[PDB]
Amino acid sequence: GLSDGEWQQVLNVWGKVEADIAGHGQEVLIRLFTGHPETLEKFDKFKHLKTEAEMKASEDLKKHGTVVLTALGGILKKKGHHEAELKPLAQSHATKHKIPIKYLEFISDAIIHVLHSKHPGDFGADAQGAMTKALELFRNDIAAKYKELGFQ
Ligand code: HEM
Image 1 (cartoon, rainbow, N blue to C red):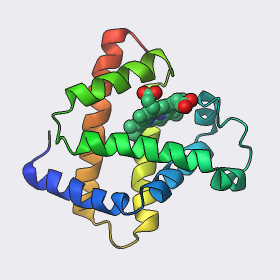
Image 2: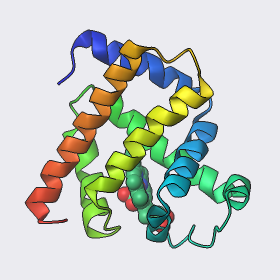
Image 3: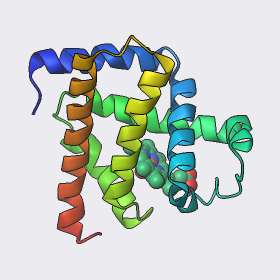
Image 4: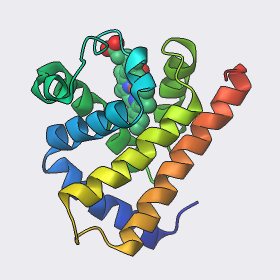
């Protein structure tokens, strides 16, 4: 549960992402894969990437970063009223991709890391608080659907 002022902060931060969605999406995924190499094994289309240079050179990885962040941005713009947008993603991630909730924690922290890396000094403590709360709400509503499905 976020206040109006917290949502305003989230959507202000998101404007930074929308100015370069592919560059942000690429870096989020590279941070996830290099920090947590087990996550790469869930992607049949990226498992061939052995080095970070190959990851950086991959145009399909940048494409997928755009898909991921476009979906997250659509959810965030709903300011918590995201049941219809979140349900299919929870279902596909539990039943088809088999993504444990832990990996959603990993990517949430990766988003925070990338925002500080690309905007040092321009991602303030209030903005980090609100973004963190928004990602926690997203993860928590997914977790509820995972529990319904019995997925661990
Ligand atoms: C911010 C969190 C995330 C968002 C918004 C997101 C969004 C999406 C979307 C929109 C798709 C395509 C449609 C679909 O299959 O439902 C996708 C595919 C996928 N997601 Fe996620 N995702 C997230 C996190 C993750 C994480 C943490 C992993 C794994 C570590 C992951 C693994 C996958 C895989 C394996 C695919 C299929 C890729 C394919 O082979 O082309 N997702 N995701």
